[PDB]
Amino acid sequence: PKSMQCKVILLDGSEYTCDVEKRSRGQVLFDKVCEHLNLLEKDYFGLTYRDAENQKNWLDPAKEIKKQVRSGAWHFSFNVKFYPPDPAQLSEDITRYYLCLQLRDDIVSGRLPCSFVTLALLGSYTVQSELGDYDPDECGSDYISEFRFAPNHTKELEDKVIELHKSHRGMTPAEAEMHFLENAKKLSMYGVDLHHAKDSEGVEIMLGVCASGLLIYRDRLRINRFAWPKVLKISYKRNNFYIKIRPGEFEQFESTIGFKLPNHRAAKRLWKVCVEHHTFFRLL
Ligand SMILES: NC(=O)N1CCN(c2ccc(F)cc2)CC1
Image (cartoon, rainbow, N blue to C red; front, side):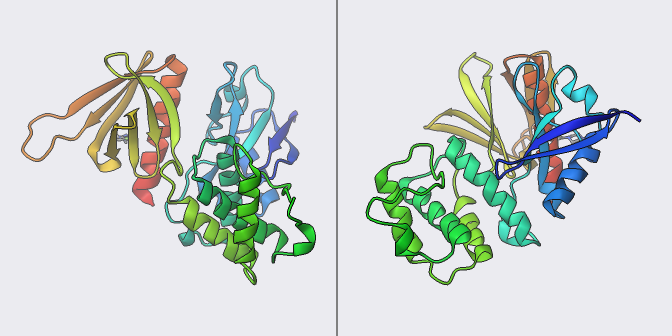
């Protein structure tokens, strides 16, 4: 029974290595990673891989690993797939911990934009969680934390993290993680998966997929939002992704909005993440 070596980048930046039979489905590897992580609330998470075009793909747990990674290495990341709109409702602290690690990467990477004050507040809760109570000993007037807090670090941001850290005396790791999440969850790009596209006139837009629906970023002045309820039907054909929108009360016919994606695989990928989010956020 021939087994393939799998390497998984965990949310703390460390590598987990295991073996699975070469005809294994993605669920087999995912179950092994989740057990390694002592994670029970597995529904929010998944494994990503990079395809032959270097795009991030979700590893489908129901399909053979080999028929997804195809010609590529058996190298994966462990990621949040469905960002809970109310992290306080998760049953375990360890779930909330992994969600925090994902969000810290979302922030440092610039996928999750954040004001100066919110970067420093989020930062201060991570420090409280990881080091415990503020200690003046590990912080002179020239302190810079090992912790990555932001896509661009400034001495002013480092100072503001420390100032807010001082206010969190007595806060336990679970408490600090919950405060982190209560703030992060409110950010306008929280849990938003962004896809480059063109509208039916060839104008460059972004399509965002999240818990509440599909977003269309045309410009800062023009953001259309389709709650899952309003979305009747979704489909892809060639390089195109089409969305059917419910008629308003006492309108006869649905509207179709068509989008052009970079290529057929980018269209299919957007279609599948939409399918997944609708099913998830219709059951949650
Ligand atoms: N198999 C079926 O009978 N349905 C058809 C509609 N479909 C859907 C998917 C995504 C979305 F955004 C809106 C609707 C769910 C599956």
